[PDB]
Image: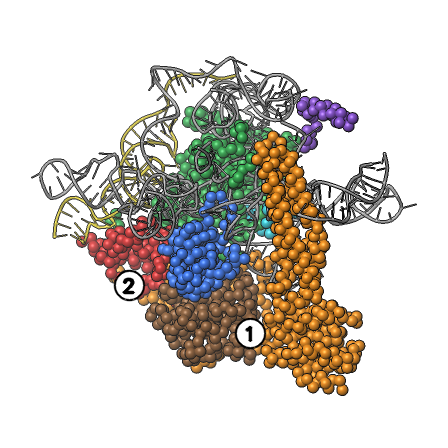
Chain colours: A cyan, B brown, C blue, D purple, E green, F red, G orange, I yellow
Amino acid sequence: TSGPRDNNRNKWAKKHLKKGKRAKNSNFSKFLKKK
Amino acid sequence: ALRAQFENSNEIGVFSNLTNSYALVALGGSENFYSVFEAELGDVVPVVHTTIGGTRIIGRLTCGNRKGLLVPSSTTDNELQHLRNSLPDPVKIQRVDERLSALGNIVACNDYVALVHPDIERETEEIIADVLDVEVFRQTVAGNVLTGSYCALSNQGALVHPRTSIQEQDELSSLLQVPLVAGTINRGSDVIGAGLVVNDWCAFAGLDTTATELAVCESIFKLQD
Amino acid sequence: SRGRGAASGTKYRMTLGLPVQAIMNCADNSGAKNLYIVSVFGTGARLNRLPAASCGDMVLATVKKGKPDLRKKIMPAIVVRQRKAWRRKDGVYLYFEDNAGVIVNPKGEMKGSAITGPVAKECADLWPRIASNAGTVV
Amino acid sequence: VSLKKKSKRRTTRLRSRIEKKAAESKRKQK
Amino acid sequence: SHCKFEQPRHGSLGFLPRKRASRQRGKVKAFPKDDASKPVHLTAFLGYKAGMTHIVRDLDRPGSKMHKREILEAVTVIETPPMVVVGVVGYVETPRGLRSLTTVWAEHLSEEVKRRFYKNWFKSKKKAFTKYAKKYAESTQSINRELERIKKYCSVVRVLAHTQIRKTPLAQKKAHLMEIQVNGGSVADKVEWAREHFEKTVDIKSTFEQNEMIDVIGVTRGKGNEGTTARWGTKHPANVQWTVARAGNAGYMHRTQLNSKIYRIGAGDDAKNASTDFDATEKRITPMGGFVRYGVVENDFVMLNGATPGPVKRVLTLRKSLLTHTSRKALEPVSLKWIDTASKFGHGRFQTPAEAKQFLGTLKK
Amino acid sequence: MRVHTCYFCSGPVYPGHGIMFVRNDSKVFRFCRSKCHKNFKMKRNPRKVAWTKAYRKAHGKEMVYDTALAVTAARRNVPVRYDRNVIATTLNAMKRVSQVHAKRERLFYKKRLA
Amino acid sequence: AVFKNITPIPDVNTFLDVVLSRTQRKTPTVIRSGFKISRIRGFYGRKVKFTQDTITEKLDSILQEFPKLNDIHPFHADLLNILYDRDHLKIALSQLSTAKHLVENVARDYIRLLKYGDSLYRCKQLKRAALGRMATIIKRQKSSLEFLEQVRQHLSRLPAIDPNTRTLLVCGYPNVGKSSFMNKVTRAQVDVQPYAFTTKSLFVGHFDYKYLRWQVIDTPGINTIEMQSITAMAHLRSAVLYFMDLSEMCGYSVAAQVKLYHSIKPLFANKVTILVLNKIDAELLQTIIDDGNVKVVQTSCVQDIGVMDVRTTACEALLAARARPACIPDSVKTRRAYDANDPNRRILARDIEAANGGAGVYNVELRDKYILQDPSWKYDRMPELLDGKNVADFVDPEIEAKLLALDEEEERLER
RNA sequence: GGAAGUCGGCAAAAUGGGAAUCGAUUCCCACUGUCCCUAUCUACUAUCUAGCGAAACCACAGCCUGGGGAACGGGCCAGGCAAAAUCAGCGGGGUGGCUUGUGGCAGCCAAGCGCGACGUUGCUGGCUCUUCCUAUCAUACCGAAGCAGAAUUCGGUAAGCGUUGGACCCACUAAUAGGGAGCUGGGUUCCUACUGAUGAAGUGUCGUCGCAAUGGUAAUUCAACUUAGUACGAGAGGAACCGUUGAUUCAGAUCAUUGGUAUUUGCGGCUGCCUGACAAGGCAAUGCCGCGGAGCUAUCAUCUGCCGGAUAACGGCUGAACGCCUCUAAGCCAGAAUCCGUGCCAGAAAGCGACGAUU
RNA sequence: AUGUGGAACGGGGUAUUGUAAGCAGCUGCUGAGAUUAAGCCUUUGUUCCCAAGAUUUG
């Protein structure tokens, strides 16, 4: 099985970070940031 | 008669239990199994996505009919509360303090008559008659104690081992007041209960069930109309 | 393929208490009485580590005492009970008072018909056939 | 850096052995 | 001649030297990358390991073997009283690294942070920061100049904050002072946020929010000098090389546990912090009889999964994760069902004395 | 999530605490701590072990019955449909158990003192 | 008999290169003259032995994977007769086995002489003398290895037949509608072209009827193809499906087809033939009809009419030769079957899933389907424990009444 | 769990014993830390201190790499390097540029200079251990093949990471690939290194908070759910990518829960002993037994293990050389578990910055 | 180096064991008694002690 150094695994991990899967962290940061 | 597979397993009786008033499906796996059951019984009876004791063998752990449902001792309070909320009011639920926890393996019960493991407790038999409102009879199937797993019951038909004799066939039919046929499910597997779940108007078997076997179940269960 | 053959679900890590050379009770009605552990499926490359099994694991078993025709096959066996205490993932610690198991084919349906004694739910979940043919599942 | 697998510099026995056996090769072809 | 029977290496070459950490407080060797798209927010906090317990939570993990079941997990309780911001440090990027250009301190420094500057507070004449206080009162235009310097030249803004160790039931009186990098916004925005946060307390309620994934960093427990057996896991003419396992220090090393989940951030002023929607039963996070070797938790606390480095009453640093990692374990919510506060000093059997008293008879005392 | 009762001491058994033992007759025993588990292993009768609630209640050292509030508790094997009004007033009935049981606990020991 | 599992046979050069490369790469390579003579002898002995082991390992793989013509069902044995000349195939396989034994003999001989090697050189040439003889042995079966590879390639193409199961052999004149009947009956995509004898070899196709599966084997029309067709019906418990061109649109005369069927009747005996009138839409036949076993079924090949009736008749002939009130809900009597394409079809949780992130991401709400006096509380958390007691033990629809009765009682005790 | 250890029941536990064959051997039962797999407890030593106080050994000493014809060595050559004084451990240090994958005899040619190359034809030692190499068994990615699918064969880059448990045998495993540089059996009659621990010292002094040159580096494999009984296949059979869940091995932590440990000699019980007696306690080289907090600990318990560039095999774009063509010559794109960083550990005790006070 | 100061005891909580001696009449006092930090928590409790000696520092 491909490891974590895999360039593919890095690529779709980047794809996850490119979409709303990290938008739950943006608004999460904004909540404390505003309060 | 329909063909379905829970995950990639030919045993759907183990992972689900079906009656004439409700359906129970395993939780946490693929709901494709829940999707298939809803496709045929969603508009008829409620379908409950339930587990029993944090376990997916609810089909062989719980035995019930169109009237009542039974759960073993290991059933958690949260799951029992979940089942009560899901099922409609005219259906009653009962915990059983039975040593033989596998209710689905020790009790094969239709709406009117149930045949039970020979060594069942008297208190279990009394509460079964009270809740299920069926006549209870202690007998073995083909010399084998697990009646619920080795025999499938419906209102109009039933199946047993191909190993049973003709006189045992006649005696079982006479004691059950329902047509009974010696057959097999899932291409030669003699666990009829584990491979077949049947209500009074539809039947589900594993996808590996042969066409001849499906014709046999359809013939005995009169489901063409 | 025997390794996770017809498991219908993953197993959680469980305390290992039945290594090889173990002698343990037959739990089915097929006629066998005692089993001897020869090897366990799914053991990797660990230096000096004795292969071990838990509840619901599939092992290679030899019927030391039992019916002669039941013997002369290194048959797959499912460990259904274990004396060593193990942590169920919900938190409770469980241990049956004897080490028990069933003679099964490589596919995962046993030669027996009814199980005498309690059955671990981990065993009953990786092996729906054992759950189907179990009498009391705990 | 050498950037090689085999060293370009030679040992004194090795360099002396060439003149030992190169001369014998001329003796043999003669 | 080759090795006949091979095995993986008995140790890890990435953690040596196995020497004693040159620090007692957990160092942050990496702060999360900054971004001007997001304005101001902090990135770290400092707490004390009070003790650890176990909880029961309903696991909503889609696709899991135990989806929608009740699960038991060990949890670590870290008391996190609010920390007072007393300084700001500007860091300028140079071809030689990040260099601290200047530092600005708040006018009123508590004895908590003043004790950090002395090895013996009682003998000292307490002369630290006195002339700084004098010049702060006299002329604020000077201090405005260093802040102008920070917002004009510096690229990284960090705030010096000290923990109110007085609030904790610790016998230590020195406050732990560290730098938390202000991530987000322009350098001017960070400088302003530092200014309006001078001398005020920043609490864990504003730093972390009960669901995110953090890195917990600290110094591990000390096991003393140990032989090759327990230090390393051990079962041609040359000189001994560094790779050979040897006998020496085992324990008290700086470690970093990644991917720790906060199951709960409770408030000290609230008396329901140990109670959940499935439990009621008014109780506090402190176990019956008090935490073993720590005391009673009376301030804000954080409940992490698993175990964290170091023994009880040691200081831990909690930082935001450097890299986003959207594993569904890191993204799922947590709904606590029950928290264990029985006596950890022995085989405890009762959650609170109130509910112990009905079961037990009328004690003569 | 059930706070069971130990077989030996008859005390509460919370999640995580204690041991579960399954016998060949499929009977499940729960032990709160190592003391009760090992005492069960040595097979010491709870009715003859002094510090057990089983001994205290079977030796006359604990109340014969407490029909507190016309109903005190039971192992209900028929689940009941979830209601707020039922769920809130039974939350109150919980407490009303506790003071009443606490009151009778004081009265009984005061009677036993003389 | 699935002949696809035979490993591909390299030509003599690649075989030698693979063997020698494996010997070089897997065995140690460096030796010095100053080493003990035992180590030198062992060094070269390993290479000779390792090369022997690689060669037999490959040669045995061939000898085991090929089917033993004698031990197999005579249908396939005779089919391999007509296609491959069992004697040539048997000679080719025996040559490899004789080679295998020769490779073993040379290696045993040279290992034996190596025990007496006195210098690094005399061992070196025994090894060179060894491997060369091993190689020259292999080079002599160039024809045998090439032949077996060609046989292998065509074997992998043959259909997997099973005479044990019920069958119905279809044979007749070339392009006389038999291919059309096979295509209409079975799912097999048999190519139909104007070129005669388009079906060079046999074509096996399964068909499900009468709750059973029958393997219809179409044979070449009637040469090697004709011989293979004859052997197909030679040993098979099946019925003939002869198709005679009624209108002669296939290019073959009806009288000629009848004469051919009469001549082939000796091999078609013990079977229920069919007197198919092919190309119905598009005298001599009296003698064929006099047999009786042939079923005269019209086959309108142009109009594709009667093919299903003929197939059903042939299948039937082959088979012959070989108080409990079920209160079904009213909604069940008018339930629309869940078929995806229709718009009236309701939704399923499977479709909610693919919309809401698919498998492993969608969290099914278990509580979403509770029979309950409200849909809002549908996410509430029911208290389970309170002050050492479960809330569950006390959930009673009349629990308020027990509390008021009680109130009165406590008010009595305080007074 | 019960000899799975070892050449082997060496030693302990069963109290040693039951049956066979010639005291020995075997077998079945029995027992157990020999082992999986180590953990805990006690005493002594080692540690420090007061006093006393040696000996062996000693040309001089003390870092490594390549070379010094040899004998390479520590002194010599060329490099890496190199900062006082020390402490506790552990014992390391006291002969071809060979070689590899393709046998021996005869003849026919015949590029060419009597030979004559390739061809062509004729015949019969094992138990544990650090690191390195690739000449790759598995894992990653590619090319070819009757490669429909699945499974597979060969070949290329590739040494990052694994390559077991038992008596050639039989299992597991993804695989059980090949080699280089403390110990025991049958067979012949000081100093230096390594590992931890202090430590004087510029920078005025003492501190607090930091920076980061450099050195080390870590994660590995499997199967489970859909995607599927779909692509493909007459059928038999039947995958993949995205997404998700567990487990094997390894690594780093931790002691809520569970087990273990008992000098808490904490409590209790039993035997014997000690004052006239009811009692009262106390004693027995840790008298014996049960429980036993705290601590320690267990893949016997729990937790945690991540992303950016540059490439190799290889697939392409434009495009000449060579008016065509061309992945290459100038340039460019995609591309492997690979290399380099990030992250993680250490912090130059002769690298540094900011701040505080300053007799 | 006079303080939300420290220390020695004491109380309480929490734990370990199992219901003490005695008073008595197995039972009651008595889930009692004993131990509880030596690397458990707490203290409007009492008592006690510290605003000292030496050394190195531009």
Q: Residue at x 22, y 57 (%)?
A: F59
Q: Is residue G10 above or below residue B203?
A: above
Q: Residue at x 43, y 39 (%)?
A: E311
Q: Which mark is residue E116?
A: none
Q: Residue at x 73, y 23 (%)?
A: D19
Name the front one of labels 1 and 2: 1
* Amino acid residing under circle 1: Thr
Structural distance between the alpha carbons of marks 1 and 2: 63 Å
Q: Which residue is mark 2?
A: F67
Residue E237, percent from left and from top? 53, 28
Quadrant placement of the C terminus of chain G:
bottom left
Badge 1: chain ID: B
* Amino acid residing under circle 2: Thr
Residue E40, percent from left and from top? 59, 42
Using residue G213 as the reference point, say whether residue E134 is left or right of it. left
Residue E89, percent from left and from top? 57, 33
Q: Secondary structure at mark 2?
A: loop
The crowd level at tag 1 (other Cα within 10 Å; few <14, some 14-19, many 20+) is some
Q: Which residue is mark 1?
A: B212
Q: Is residue G136 above or below residue I2?
A: below
